[PDB]
Amino acid sequence: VYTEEDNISQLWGLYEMSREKLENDDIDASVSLVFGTIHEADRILRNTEDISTLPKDFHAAYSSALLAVSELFEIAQKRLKETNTEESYIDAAIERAQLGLDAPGNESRLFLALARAYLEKVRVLVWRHDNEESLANIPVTQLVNPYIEKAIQYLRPLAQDSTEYFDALTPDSLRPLYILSSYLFQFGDQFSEAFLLDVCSIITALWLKSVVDPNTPAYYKLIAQEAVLNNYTTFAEYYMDLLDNVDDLINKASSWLNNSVDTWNVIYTLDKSPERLLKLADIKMDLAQIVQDEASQDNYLKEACNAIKEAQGSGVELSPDYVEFVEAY
Ligand SMILES: [Cl-]
Image 1 (cartoon, rainbow, N blue to C red):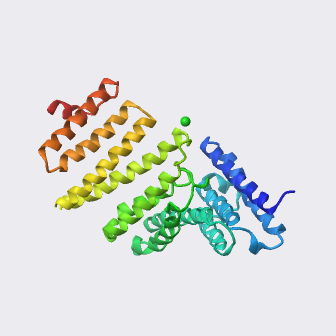
Image 2 (cartoon, protein in one colour; image 1 turned 180 degrees about the vertical axis):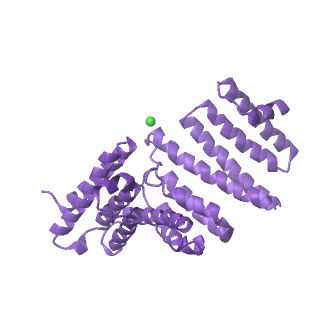
Image 3 (tube, rainbow, N blue to C red; image 1 turned 45 degrees about the vertical axis):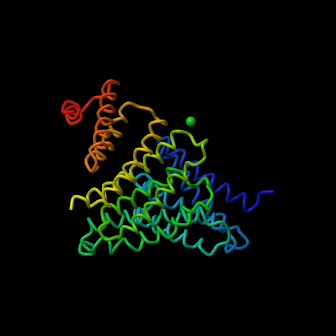
C-alpha cells in the first residue's frame, strides 16, 4: 500500500528534484517542481484523516518549497497574480515551518527549514532598510536581531554531534549561512567575543557536517570547505583589526590563520590547482605581518614566496602586487 509516510517521502522527492534541476541551471523546471511540491502538500492536507498527526517532516518540505519560490521568484512570479511578492513567500515559509513545531516526529529537517527561512527574512529586511523610506531610521540591528536570534535557536541543535547527518543538510541548503556570516561581520561590533566564537563554531560545524560522509563527492566537499576557510579567515581579520587599535589578539589571530592553512590544505588536496597557491601566500603573509618572532616571520615569508613562485611557474598570472613581493624578497 501507499502510506502517509510514503506520500511525505514522495513530497521530499519532488523538492529534491527541484534542487537537482536548479543545480543544472534549469530554473523553469525547478520552478515547476517547486509549485508541484506545494500542490502535492495541499493535496495531502485535504486527504489526511488528522492534520494534527502530519509529522514535522511534512511541514519542513512544504516550508522548503515556499522558500524556494522566493529564491526563484524572478521566474516564478510569471505564473502568479501580480499581488504576490518574494517576501510574502519567505513569510509563508516561516509560518508553514512554525506550524510544524507542534507536529509529531524528528525535528532536524524542520529546524533547518526554520533557520533557512529566518535568514532569508534577514536578508530581505536589510534590503528594505536600505530602500524603503519607512524603515530608513530604524537601526538594522534592531530590525533583524529577532530573526538572527531565531535562526541561531534552530541551528544550534543541528550543529551538535548528537544530531546525526540527514540528507536535507547539503552544502546548497546551507547557502543562507552566508547571510549570517555577513551579518556578524558587518555588525559584530555589537556582540561580545564569546557570542561570536559561539555562533561561528555553529556555522562551521554545520558546513563540516554537510559533507562528513567520506563518500561525499569532491565537488560538494569543496563548497563546504571553502565556506569554512572563509569563516576562519574572517575571524582572523576580526582579531587583526582589533590589533590595529596585545599578545592575546596576536595569539588568537594566529590560531585562526593557522586553522585557515589547515583547511586550505584540505581544499588543495581536493581540487589541486596552481592558482590556489596565491590564497596560501596571502594567509602566510598575514601570519608574517603580525608574528612577534623574527624566526617565524622569516619562515612565513619564505613559504609565501615559494607559493607565489610555484604558481607563476605553473602558468598562473601574477598581479604587480605578487610580482613585487617576490622581487623585494
Ligand atoms: Cl568524487
